Amino acid sequence: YGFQPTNGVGYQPYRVVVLSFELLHAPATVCGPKKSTNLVKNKCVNFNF
Amino acid sequence: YGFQPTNGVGYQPYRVVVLSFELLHAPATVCGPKKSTNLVKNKCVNFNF
């Protein structure tokens, strides 16, 4: 490449990262800040197990 | 000014410094990177006093 600070757009260097990840194949182990709550029973509730 | 990294030449910021010299009126105190020599006399020589 010929990266020079005087070059116009379409020639300046860009930094690129691609994120790939499997939806589900096993016990998942990568995810963010969801607060693990307690456990309730014998009631109609919604859950995010 | 509207300096943006996407701006083309003729709009990116430039840094400028100007140096002005007075042409000597007193014992000078800003000399070049020269080294002095011993003093001779009674001989045809050239000098840089």
Image (spheres, coloured by chain):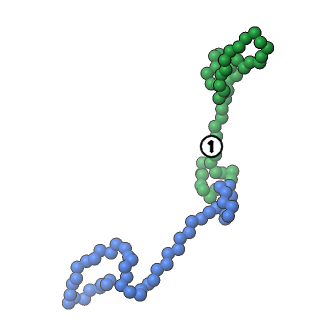
Chain colours: A blue, B green
User: Which residue is at a point 70% across and 22% down the rendered structure image?
Assistant: B23
Give the quadrant of the C terminus of chain B. top right
User: Which residue is at a point 66% across and 27% down the rendered structure image?
Assistant: B34
User: Which residue is at a point 65% across and 29% down the rendered structure image?
Assistant: B33
Q: Using residue A35 as the reference point, say whether residue A21 is left or right of it.
A: right
Residue B47 position, x and y percent, is 74, 18
Tell me the element at label 1: loop
- According to the picture, the residue beneath numbered tag 1 turns out to be B15
State whether residue A33 is above or below residue B32.
below
How many numbered circles does the render carry?
Answer: 1
In this view, which residue lies farthest toward the right? B44
State whether residue A44 is above or below residue A34.
below
Residue A30 position, x and y percent, is 39, 77
Q: Quadrant of residue A16?
A: bottom right
Residue B35 position, x and y percent, is 65, 25
Nearer-the-camera pick, B49 or A9: B49
Q: Taking the image as drawn, is residue B40 in sight?
A: yes
State whether residue B40 is above or below residue A27.
above
State whether residue A6 is above or below residue A48.
above
Badge 1: few (under 14), some or many (20 or more) residues near its Cα, within 10 Å?
A: few
Residue A43 position, x and y percent, is 22, 88
Q: Taking the image as drawn, is residue B25 in sight?
A: no
Q: Quadrant of residue A32?
A: bottom left
Which chain letter matches label 1? B
* Disc 1 residue type (three-letter): Arg
